[PDB]
Amino acid sequence: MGSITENTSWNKEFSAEAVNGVFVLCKSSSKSCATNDLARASKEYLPASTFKIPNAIIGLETGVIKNEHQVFKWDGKPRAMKQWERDLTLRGAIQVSAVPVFQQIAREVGEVRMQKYLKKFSYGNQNGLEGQLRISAVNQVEFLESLYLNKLSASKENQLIVKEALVTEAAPEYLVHSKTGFSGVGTESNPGVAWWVGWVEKETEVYFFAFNMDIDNESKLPLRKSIPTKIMESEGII
Amino acid sequence: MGSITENTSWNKEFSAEAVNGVFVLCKSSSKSCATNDLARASKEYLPASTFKIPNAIIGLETGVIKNEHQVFKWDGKPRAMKQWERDLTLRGAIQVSAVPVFQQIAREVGEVRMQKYLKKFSYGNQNISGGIDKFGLEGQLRISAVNQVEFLESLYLNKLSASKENQLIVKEALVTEAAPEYLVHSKTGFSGVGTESNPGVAWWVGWVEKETEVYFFAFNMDIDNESKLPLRKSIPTKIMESEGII
Ligand SMILES: [Co+2]
Ligand SMILES: [Co+2]
Image (cartoon, rainbow over all chains, first blue to last red; front, side, top):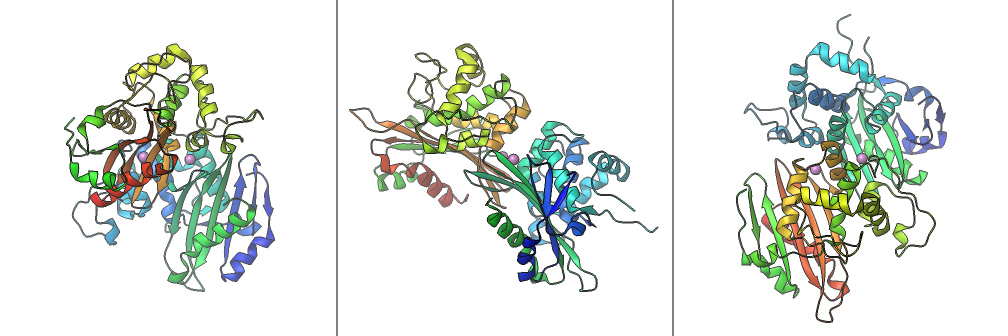
């Protein structure tokens, strides 16, 4: 966000769970973010399901998604996960991380048009067989800020629609917009990535966060939520 | 639309607690509603804090509220509730039910423009007389449950005489519980207590997004004792739970 600061005490939470990752946190009025690893904060990883955010905005922007009330009806073919084998709203599709739904959105937007929006959005970047899209935590928090401030190259309507769909928790005092990613299990040599991106609105303040971690045990996935919670709890947030 | 339908069956929980109230419930796809009392459903009551919903939209439309990231700054003047003595966002001012913040908005909106948008929303009997900004809590403005539900349907579907973006802002301001399987939008209302013949009213109005479906509700009850209040939340819940919603 301009200047990024190291908070090495955060690493205690990671080390207690034997997890290699990075948490990035930004207070909105600060225009400067904090982290546990300076080098890993700006390091680019596959967005996985977190890509469903810029996906949903382009999908609306192109008219591929007509409006917020559009249902994505199940065609009949057996999908990879059971949770996906039902009709879905926009929030439904996002929260169950229904890949096929967004694959179909991605097809009828197009590879070139998608790329045009990703450029404008400044969402991650590309790299001679393919070169998959990767994104840095620093880029996530920058991304979500522009989404929150309504400052993306999209209508405010379309940004607002996606934001409600990103609502994951709600209490009288705070509102949590978040999205999870998981690229798959990996090895110790070559690990998968787990994401949690979002922001926490509390009081008159806003905190943007991007967390990622190496994952080589199925069982450690839920840690993508406890590490960022325990840090934000002791920071004095939630 | 479709219809409303008395179902005395729900009265169970009301008798259970000696509560004179009404629930309206409406399946959106079915385009139809269901209640315990057709008579009380159409009976118009003081909106109280449920009135913040319209006031938010009128405030956004009129430019009074600049946008969703507007901060309503606390001057340092004492307020009736500890919870109001802090700076507030839109969601904040709606959640803690901050009377003075919204009273300020009503006054910057004016009687004229408050009539304008309230006419356009078909909000209640639309009658705002008496006091420039008291019409919600202890004024002349009154609204039915069915009307609440009607209004809230128009909000969900962005059908109001107000821009979509302002409609979406307030819709987010109303999120009160989020789960993977469903989302919840509501406001509470509460006019006061006691009798001297005439008892107070207590509202809970919202809608629930469950899978592909969505259920609109408005609820009110008669309150003469302060304690039976949480039943404004719990009773409508218990019924939705039985009907299989949450
Ligand atoms: Co928000
Ligand atoms: Co909603």
